[PDB]
View 1 (tube, rainbow, N blue to C red):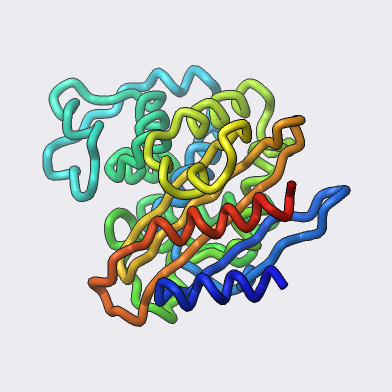
View 2: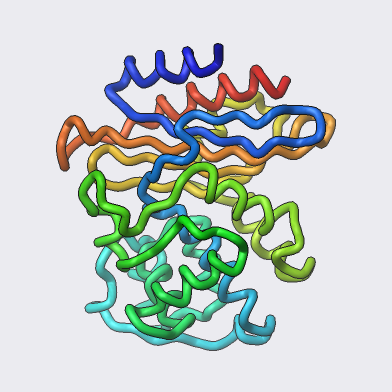
Amino acid sequence: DLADRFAELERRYDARLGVYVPATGTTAAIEYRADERFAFCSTFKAPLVAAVLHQNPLTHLDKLITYTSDDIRSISPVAQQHVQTGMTIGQLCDAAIRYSDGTAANLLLADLGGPGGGTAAFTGYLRSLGDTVSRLDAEEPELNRDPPGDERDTTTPHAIALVLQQLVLGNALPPDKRALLTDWMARNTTGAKRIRAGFPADWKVIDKTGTGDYGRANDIAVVWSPTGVPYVVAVMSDRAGGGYDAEPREALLAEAATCVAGVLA
């Protein structure tokens, strides 16, 4: 019956909806197009900082990185202000998650090294968690512009949700590094109108957003019920029917999250 509401929301916005919530001890798994490929967009910026944290000691966060105005190639609210001073690896992680800074994302990919500016090393990290589906092939901002049907720079709600589960609720990272990831996602500034807007205020929400062309709008989150039970929620969408210039619809992601909150209640 819940699958009839998601398809109802798809009718209302000219959209394709993808939803996955991992199953817990007391609740079954929610799935709607869970194994269909959607574009990463800015969703990869959360597991990316976990990759840098995984391969480096906490002192690596103090290394200063220098760049020029010809490295700013996408939406970068933070990197545009430090082209003279430079930014530490620590501040690059902070800006990449809480402000979705595109330039900080590309610099962190260079910090992972390897061919393709780090895209190979990053995908290798997801394979190490058990994700044999997701893949990153380009950098910002080209990773947001792959045509519909192309597998480059794509994931699925099923795959990214299980990866997020290991990073926040599992042991993919030691506690010291795990507390840095969670706090940054908890002080996000870009997701006020998506998953967060669909859940009651007494539910705690941490999230990382994504947006691109063809009306692509994503949000991945970990939520806590008022009593303290955790869940993982992945919601992705696009509107390829309207072409390259289709506008993303945030209200669709908020309304779908309300439907999830009704079942978990």
